[PDB]
Amino acid sequence: SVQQQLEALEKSSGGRLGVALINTADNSQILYRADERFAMCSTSKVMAAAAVLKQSESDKHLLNQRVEIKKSDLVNYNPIAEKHVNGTMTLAELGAAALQYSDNTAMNKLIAHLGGPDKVTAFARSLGDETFRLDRTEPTLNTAIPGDPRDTTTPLAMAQTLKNLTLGKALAETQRAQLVTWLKGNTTGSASIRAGLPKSWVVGDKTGSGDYGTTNDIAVIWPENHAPLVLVTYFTQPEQKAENRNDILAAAAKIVTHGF
């Protein structure tokens, strides 16, 4: 009947909804189209940030390395990087900006530092994620064309990988804690998953949006008196210029967490 509710939400919305919830208390799962590919858009930024944190495990100087920001580095959405044109940002600062403000220049800097989109994909494979693929940089990784496999993953794969990154064995403790700190400080997710949950729950999330009204959020959730939940909600539509629908993600989160 959670299934019935998600199916009715999807039908009314006129799009395609993908949901994966992992309850880490018993490793039970609520899945809806969790095996289907969706364009990740900005939710892919988490993997690029994590790949740099993994590097920092063996290179104690990495996170403080400075990167020059020039006018030509700027793409189409740079709320943090534009404040530093002609100056520099550390890799840690780029990580923060990519995740907490969804800065596109910060994402591209991280990808260039790693050596390209294929390097983010190899990082994901090393974590046992055989689904994730990053193919392009910002801003073209957001085209989200139906049936296009580029820059996609599935809700289940992303839920498992986010669990491993934030609560599991993917990163050493210091790096794991840094990633979690970044996600909890996200500024862009108020109208998404967070809006469907009790106000007192602690949430770390990364949103993403793109063409075809593609509207995504992935979250780690710490309830007050229970083990954490991991929740991925992906949503996309059939018209290229469809409006983004953060309210659909909030509604889906309310449905699947009804019971906690």
Image: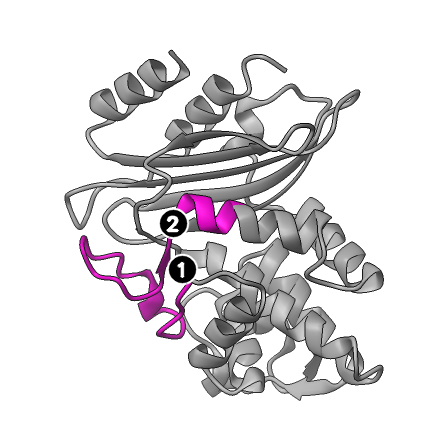
Q: Position of residue 32 (x, y in %)?
A: 36, 31
- Magenta segment boundaries in residue numbering: 131-159
The reply to whether discs 2 and 1 touch (Cβ–Cβ < 8 Å) is: yes
Secondary structure type for disc 2: loop
Q: Earlier in the sequence, mark 2 or mark 1?
A: 1
Residue holding disc 2:
154
Q: Is residue 144 visible?
A: yes
**Above or below, 250 relative to 180:** above
Residue 47, numbered label: none
**Above or below, 38 relative to 227:** below
**Above or below, 243 relative to 110:** above
Residue holding disc 1:
131
Give the amino acid at mark 2.
Thr
Lateral position of residue 145 relative to residue 210, left or right = left
Q: What residue appears at the point 22 percent right and 41 percent down from the top-left corner? A: 237
Q: Position of residue 45 (x, y in %)?
A: 52, 62
